[PDB]
Amino acid sequence: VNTALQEVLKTALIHDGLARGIREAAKALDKRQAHLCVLASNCDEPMYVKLVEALCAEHQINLIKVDDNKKLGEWVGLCKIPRKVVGCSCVVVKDYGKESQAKDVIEEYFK
RNA sequence: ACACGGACAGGAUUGACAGAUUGAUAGCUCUUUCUCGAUUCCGUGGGUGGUGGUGCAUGGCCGUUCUUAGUUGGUGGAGCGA
């Protein structure tokens, strides 16, 4: 179910909890402070970015996958609702709020 | 300053060491290539700022006629009337 991206990300932007972007993801992985990693599977061909795929096998990070760039850019960050299209490709969530329905679905996804 | 659109987390873009530059220890810019991460940059519209004009569009205030001793109603008289 997709409330593992609806109930954590929209409640996570309000708390200085997003590290959105790609080089900031590399500096956040070297901080050892990645707790939640939303990848991309949308690319020109996906073999061009292998750094966030391999630095978690050095750094023991949880990974949750998605297949989309534009619905990723509609999950997190800003947009007009002639429309301001930006697209996000990798998300490090650094911090959270206090949640009682959605701690587990980001927590227990270790398969 | 805002709004429309271009841009844009495959990064809008702020800061910056040495070296040319300069009168300069102005990342000013050019060489050079790191930091930052949607406040920000591109053209429009509209604005803002002015100890810039016109005291001959004006107020406020001040000088001067004048600190000389002048100025005006009401009822009554004069005049059709000023």
Image (cartoon, grey):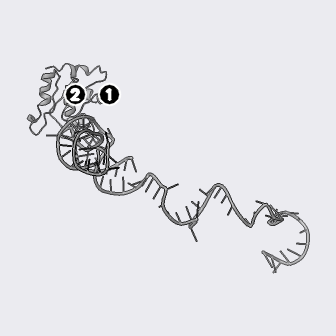
- Would you place residue B37 above or below residue B74 in this image? above
Q: Looking at the image, which residue is at 16% across and 22% down?
A: A59
Is A51 situated left or right of B18 in this image? left
Quadrant of the image occupied by residue B63: bottom right
Mark 1 neighbour density, 10 Å: few (under 14) some (14–19) many (20 or more): few
Q: Nearer the viewer, residue B12 or B45?
A: B12
Amino acid type at image mark 1: His
Secondary structure of residue under mark 2: helix
Quarter of the view holding residue A31: top left
Q: Quadrant of residue A92?
A: top left
Residue B77 locus on image (x, y percent): 91, 72
At a point 23% along the width and 19% down the height, the residue shown is A104
Q: Secondary structure at mark 1?
A: helix
Using residue A39 as the reference point, say whether residue A102 is left or right of it.
Answer: right
Q: Are both tags, 1 and 2, on one chain? A: yes
> Which residue carries the number 1 mark?
A15
Pinpoint the chain carrying mark 2. A
Q: Is residue A85 visible?
A: no
Q: Rounded to the nearest whole Å, what is the CA distance between mark 1 and mark 2?
A: 17 Å
Residue type at mark 2 is: Ala
Q: On what subunit does the disc labeled 1 rest?
A: A
What is the crowding at mark 2: few (fewer than 14 residues within 10 Å), some, or many (at least 20)?
some
Question: Which residue is painted at 22% across and 27% down in the image?
Answer: A28
How many marks are shown on the rendered structure?
Answer: 2
Question: Which quadrant, please, contains the C terminus of chain A?
Answer: top left
Which residue is more in the foreground, A32 or A98?
A32
Q: Residue beneath label 2, please?
A: A28
Image height check: is B26 above or below B46?
A: above
Pointer 1 or 2: first along the chain: 1
